Image 1 (spheres, one colour):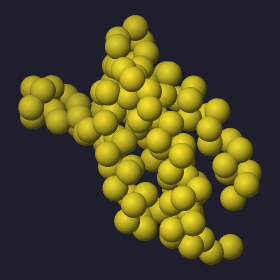
Image 2 (cartoon, one colour):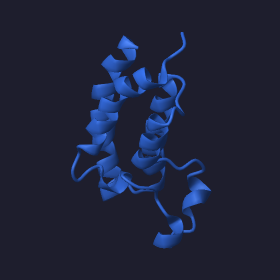
Image 3 (cartoon, one colour):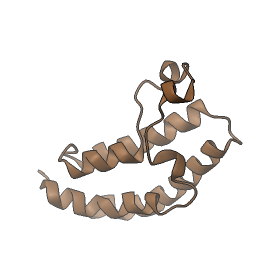
Length: 114
């Protein structure tokens, strides 16, 4: 099965929009973590492969996911990075958990249809 790039984008986009719709929970995820601006030099020692919503959106818009599971892997990468780096009761961690709840609800039927 070979996916047409614009069809894959159309099918997956609503799941990404669902994440952006979460306010305030998407706010820490709408742009990359910048350890230099934040002064957290330990971040890239723990998070080897950073990911965020803006990067996923760009990849989804520019034919970078040839198969749906590649998009799903990047969403989970974003979540797992945040859940590894941050305290469980931190705002980021709690917001991450809400996005993951929304994502699983939205993605499951889409992947079955694809």
